[PDB]
View 1 (tube, rainbow over the protein chains, first blue to last red):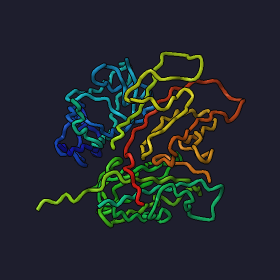
View 2: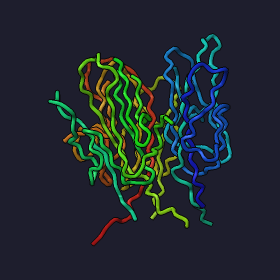
View 3: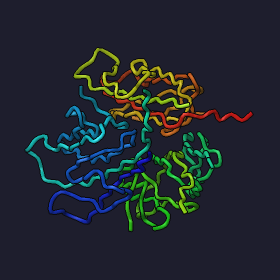
View 4: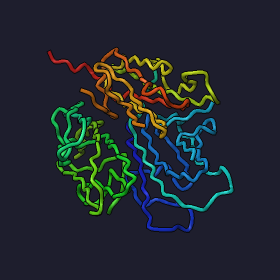
Length: 131
Length: 131
Length: 131
């Protein structure tokens, strides 16, 4: 079968938000899949996909680690402003769920950054079962 | 049909140029397609291609926006040293033409940077017509 | 035929190492292929692949240049902390070998960085012989 899925959201809101940031630029994103507000990504994709996150500079400090499914830790979108760090590929399980942790010190300053999350299907695995 | 096209030019000229910068490294680029001097890209590709631009840091200021076809604005190779910004995907029309605007303030300094422009065919769309 | 190869190693070693750095996170890498300790990449792949190296900032200086096969020089993983620089494509020969040169000054500082080396097979060439 061919699942033909792509997803890509962009953010360009005008000024100061009342809270957590949504997305208004559906650039291609037929099913929705990953809710980017809570970051709860259900991939049914089950092939090799091409992933690209946009990292906000924030030289002011604070450690950002996007938790990865099956192991915890495993910062794949890693920024230091059993466990491995990877950028290009994607050991993601079918139906499993990634979650962003943004809590690494409480003596911080208030700031709201802007984030772009693209992610397009490259290869859907075609059965690949032998006996 | 299979159009089997790739294009990728590179720049490694020795020193100070008399004007606008050409390309001597045809890395793979059978037809030529995009003239990178005037930046006039005719894509007959008409499927999904994988685009990667190389962004020169230039912290000194000046806003750089590569104009996109069909809408104007639409900075896809965006650097802030109807309208959306995208990096991974490519809504490009068949036969349409992209152009680089490099004019955002006239009280600037003279500098000549070096730029690498790759772009390879991933998927040619195979008819995809039903009735 | 279907060559079905992917390769990607990751590094998350705990602290201060006695020399050149190996890899403990085989994330997907069935044959192994490229030993990144000695940097001796044997591609039998013979196809167009998408390779991406992670560049350590190192603002302190020192010229980094990864030698490319068939020409010498030709820095493909280029960082300025007949010869061309390319990021996306790969004019690489079957069975030939790329090597990192890390020697551009002797009056420097001692440092150890951590490096992640991904590289995934996009297209295996399917004969493409006519007469």
